[PDB]
Amino acid sequence: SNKCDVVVVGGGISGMAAAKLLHDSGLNVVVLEARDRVGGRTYTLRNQKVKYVDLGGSYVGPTQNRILRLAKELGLETYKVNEVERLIHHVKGKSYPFRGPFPPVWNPITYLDHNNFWRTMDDMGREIPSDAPWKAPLAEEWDNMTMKELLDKLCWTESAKQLATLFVNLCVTAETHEVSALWFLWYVKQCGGTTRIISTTNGGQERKFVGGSGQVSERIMDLLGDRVKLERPVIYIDQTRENVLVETLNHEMYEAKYVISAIPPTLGMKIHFNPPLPMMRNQMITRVPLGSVIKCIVYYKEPFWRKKDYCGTMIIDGEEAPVAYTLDDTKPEGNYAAIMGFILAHKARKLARLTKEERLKKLCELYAKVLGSLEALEPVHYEEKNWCEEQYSGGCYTTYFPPGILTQYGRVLRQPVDRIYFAGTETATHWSGYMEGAVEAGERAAREILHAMGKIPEDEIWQSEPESVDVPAQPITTTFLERHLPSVPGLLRLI
Amino acid sequence: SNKCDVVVVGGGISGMAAAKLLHDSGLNVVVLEARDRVGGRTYTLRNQKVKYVDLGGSYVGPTQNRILRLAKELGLETYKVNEVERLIHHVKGKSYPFRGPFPPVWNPITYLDHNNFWRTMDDMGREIPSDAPWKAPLAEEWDNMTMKELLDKLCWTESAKQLATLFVNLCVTAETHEVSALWFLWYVKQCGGTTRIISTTNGGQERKFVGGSGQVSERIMDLLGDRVKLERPVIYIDQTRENVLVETLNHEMYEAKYVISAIPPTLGMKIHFNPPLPMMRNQMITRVPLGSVIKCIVYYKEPFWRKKDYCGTMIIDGEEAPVAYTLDDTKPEGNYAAIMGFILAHKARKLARLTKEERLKKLCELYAKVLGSLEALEPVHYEEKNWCEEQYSGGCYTTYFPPGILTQYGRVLRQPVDRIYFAGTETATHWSGYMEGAVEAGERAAREILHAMGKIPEDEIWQSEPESVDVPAQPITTTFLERHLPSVPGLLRLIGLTTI
Ligand SMILES: *Cc1cc2c(cc1C)nc1c(=O)[nH]c(=O)nc-1n2C[C@H](O)[C@H](O)[C@H](O)COP(=O)(O)OP(=O)(O)OC[C@H]1O[C@@H](n2cnc3c(N)ncnc32)[C@H](O)[C@@H]1O
Ligand SMILES: *Cc1cc2c(cc1C)nc1c(=O)[nH]c(=O)nc-1n2C[C@H](O)[C@H](O)[C@H](O)COP(=O)(O)OP(=O)(O)OC[C@H]1O[C@@H](n2cnc3c(N)ncnc32)[C@H](O)[C@@H]1O
Ligand SMILES: Cc1ccc(NC(=O)c2coc3ccccc3c2=O)cc1C
Ligand SMILES: Cc1ccc(NC(=O)c2coc3ccccc3c2=O)cc1C
């Protein structure tokens, strides 16, 4: 067998970040990666037609200081996603251009309803601890409802309910009826709230990495050299003896003092454990699916939308549209003009039956309607990735919690099992679901092991991160009216 | 490689029934079983204090003709669970004895609400095809709500909502907010409806096997000889070549024409697939958890409850009660007096933290109160099994579907993947979740392979079963008033219209 200090299962950002921290501390680490590549739910494709394109995770933004710091250390730079010109909200077959993060609403009743919806999501989030959402005062009540039930109670207008539904679908690649209200409200709150999570400028979608996000994992693999073993799916972990034994599908055996599991929680099912996992983890890893998304990038000769004072952001309501949300994917130089779109949740399942060429046609025709331009019908290239088909991801962007699961099983997610510690973005407390969360969790799991070895004190397990000098955060603000305008039933109680 | 016609993954009733059918038809079969035993979600413990006891699946009843025929062919016999004396409904800290399958309800408004609840569950069920629940006219609407939401709409009394909640918890070992309304409605309908599923006499809980249900799987293993390989967990299936390659954890390779996967759907995750599974199955197997239950058997010197004219059945509502349902588990000879109880859904998670001795004490104290009997505090022995801890089951009794999953992913549950066919009780269309469904699915999977091999025509894949001569099925009947009495909102409409 191959002996080392720590085996890290999974060579995504989380596993790589954990392995780098342990390596830098002087431990001998091995990373066992199932695929013939690193990066996991990140994947940057290079060819002459696109130069490079993120087909998985791409965006980073203010308050995501760990990913920004790690990438900077590895020699990467960011550029801003184009938001110079107007955004579009396409509603009932018409495009309404706008500025600022939220589409305007003109009907006074609809206005009150929309304002109340966003405000209430943040009000509720303030009572949910980031590190322990199951300790929310109404944890059980909120966990036993779906997001669909919550939106049905909160939204007096169909307009607000359709936009709220789109929000859930885009944020967590799942249907409102599939997900726990508690979990979803935690998810938003732990990215800094509604404004921060939905915003391009000053939010989660502000920036991309020059040359692609895949470079984070690739460049850590570059540092680690042959410590990274590709095409080594872990099948078996045995903790009955002095050292932990980790076996791969290609018949290799690794021996270590500790293990970090840096895979999505449910993919723990692909590993046979000796002794068996404790009851609560055994059942938890069957209760935590990942969402469904096809990421699609359509290329054009020029970023023609800019000529009509549109930035390329489209927010597209309704069942018929294949794609509910787009961003401009053009490179910083104004070349490789492109629109990135997501085919979300049930639509990913529905439209996966089509051919690549059939999806291209539907997207181009949609974009022609929304951008009001025949130029959208003349694509020069197309790339896509359906994450639902990946054996070693399970989906994208991340794991969702159905009703009842987070309160009953959430405490087990990052609880060590003897000498196995748990990384992965699902275990983060700030931007869980994102590349930022992957870094937080990997570095925390690594430091749990450093503490178990006696190398650092307990109070160094969780570590704050200085703010990025390159991507500083501006405060999230609200207006007096936003804070104090009544809800729809509030206006009725006054009548 | 060890060569054969068909590799069956899993030695539970479904895999063993499939293997038997294939073997009897002249094929060479191998059964690869992860555990050191066959039976899976069935397990019959034997020791001198209990003689034998079913710690997993136990009950069979009228309309479950496949398991009865299989068991009979293997030389097994049934006996009737004791329902001679009165049942007990324990609610708000008091016990109310009764006869008939449902506790009687006296308050007229509450009676209308209860009657409408059960009626409506069956009414909705009739809209749902047993073999394609996603084809129900309102499949989407019903699949996008939980059972909690449906009970909140349907039940105009707390009395009905509480009993309905216990019904869901007991039937599918899951909370009302955890499960899809469409899936639960399908599940009940495919067992023959509310009366059949809840009943002891004339229903699902009527009988047990003399000597334990584990004998079904054991006796098939005896017939198959060394074709059953114990402690062979499957880790890898490769369909890239002419013959299917199946690899086990202990480093053996098996080569076959076809494979039957006879394991719970989510446990497919423990196998690495080459090529990868198609998208819909890849995601489906991450979306289908099993329920949570501890099965607990408390032994006594005598079946003392019978002397108070109680049969041993207790239907126990309330958060403080660890166990919501009991049955008399005394042997047919009248010795090894015992009460079987289930600790359900969240309570299985909550009470797992205690010791065995602490759980025994809580159960005895509950039974003493419910039975009004100090004798319940004098147990002579205890056995239990927490199915939540089983790596190779995932839970019990069966797989549940959360909201939204059955309409999006249900169609791939028994869809073949190249040369892999799918058995397991989860893929049945009649008593899915039960030993019966395991037999149906195993035999159906085997015959899919026989059809693929050109050995039988397509119309023999699905095969009806003759009614048991030993366990005749009384029909499910209603009264005129049961059919036509209004719901609570229907009564309110009638009142509004009169007064107009
Ligand atoms: C898919 C996706 C993700 C995504 C998104 C859009 C799409 C289409 N957009 C994002 C965005 O704009 N900004 C952002 O910050 N995140 C975005 N996401 C999510 C993001 O990609 C993820 O949060 C992050 O990449 C997750 O990182 P983590 O390291 O936690 O997880 P992973 O990437 O899945 O890596 C796990 C690795 O483990 C390997 N594996 C799996 N099973 C095994 C076994 N048995 N043995 C050995 N290795 C295993 C995987 O192959 C993978 O490499
Ligand atoms: C657990 C339980 C079940 C149960 C019940 C009460 C409890 C506590 N009460 C029942 C009842 O009264 N009447 C009834 O008809 N059913 C009842 N249930 C359900 C019943 O036990 C199940 O429906 C039935 O036994 C399921 O049979 P099936 O053959 O479909 O599935 P299984 O028993 O789980 O068998 C699967 C076998 O596969 C093995 N396995 C798992 N993974 C692997 C891998 N990777 N490789 C090889 N083998 C694998 C398992 O070990 C098992 O033996
Ligand atoms: C009006 C509006 C604008 C942007 C958004 N965006 C989001 O919520 C996003 C949430 O998480 C993401 C994760 C990966 C990539 C993109 C996103 C979002 O844009 C939502 C609404 C309702
Ligand atoms: C009044 C009453 C009596 C029995 C039941 N029982 C049930 O629903 C059961 C359904 O599934 C089972 C599965 C395995 C073992 C036992 C059972 C039940 O008793 C329910 C009610 C509401």
Image (cartoon, coloured by chain):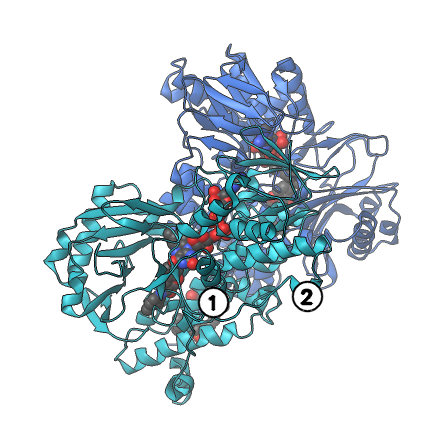
Chain colours: A cyan, B blue
Q: Earlier in the sequence, mark 1 or mark 2?
A: 1
Helix, strand or loop at disc 2? helix
Q: Nearer the viewer, mark 1 or mark 2?
A: 2
Q: Quadrant of ligand 3?
A: bottom left
Q: Is A108 displayed left or right of A490 in the figure? A: left
Task: Find disc 2 in the rendering and name its residue.
Answer: A459
The residue nearer to you, when weighing A181 against A188, is A188
Amino acid type, label 2: Asp
Residue at 41% from the left image edge and 13% from the top image edge:
B455
Q: Is residue A373 above or below residue B493?
A: above
Residue A60: percent from left, percent from top = 40, 62
Residue B2: percent from left, percent from top = 55, 14
The alpha-carbon separation of the residues under discs 1 and 2 comes to 24 Å
Residue at 46% from the left image edge and 38% from the top image edge:
A35
Residue at 63% from the left image edge and 57% from the top image edge:
A447
Q: Which of the chains bears the disc numbered 1?
A: A
Residue B60: percent from left, percent from top = 63, 33
Task: Find disc 1 in the rendering and name its residue.
Answer: A191
The answer to whether any part of residue A53 appears in the image is: yes
